[PDB]
Image (cartoon, rainbow, N blue to C red):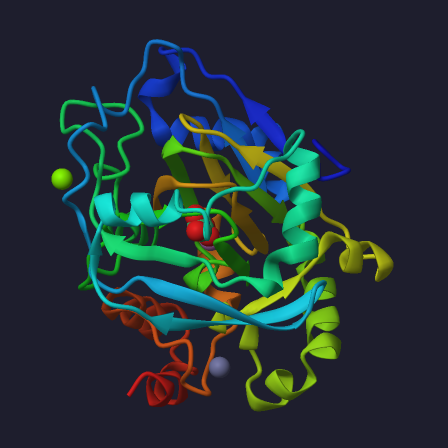
Length: 331
Ligand SMILES: O=C(O)CNC(=O)C(=O)O
Ligand SMILES: [Mg+2]
Ligand code: NI
Ligand SMILES: [Zn+2]
């Protein structure tokens, strides 16, 4: 078996190998990359996502989210308070303010220490899930706005034609902005490109050990666990690496820098934080190997997790028994 310790792999494709997305994902998996839950892909040196980022300040962040923490430094939840709309220019200015900026630090490890020590005592503002793309239409390779769609994958593999579309989303982050422990909707893959700015640190549990994370999470968030059988779909729970180590949960960590791709694999739980002002673009995608994960994915039926028009069709076709009760959560 390739990659039996489930280490995060880093790939360096040539421009020639960067021409066929599906075939490169298949290559990565041949080398065991999926076992970790997360891989990094460094694009060829000749590739660029677009010519410059000089004209992005007028993008609107219609609902910035203030991420308010509760709990203890190692084990907390965050709630997202809606703030008034601001442009990307306004947001970058706010991110760079004395109140919100990244503190002085030695290296990524000192900054990670400061994050886990101090996160709960601040409420950074996140511009998340903004439909859109920053790829130039003339970028032909690994353009997250031109991938083949999950609907077409289901059609090619399974023969069923469904409604729905699949488009990318932009994330504008600042110091301490946080993504809680989750897998993707319907345990899909995701791909994330860091377009500009400061890094993003990721933590990931191997898919083969996801249930161990869930068991710990039920113990650490006992009331949430009673209220919903898949409460990590709410995307509010944080657990530090120290706590994961104390409880024997296998995981890995890696820092993504501007100009690099990350791929998360089906049922790879991940969490992380941003080092300072940045902009990422991400989209879900599927392969043939995904199909059985889609059939087995947990679902939120307390109704908190509340998810897309397009995810309806996936649940209807892959999880017809759940469909009924699931749609009660979403209506
Ligand atoms: O970048 C973020 O804030 C979160 N991204 C993801 O969880 C992802 O790409 O799967
Ligand atoms: Mg603009
Ligand atoms: Ni994700
Ligand atoms: Zn729920």
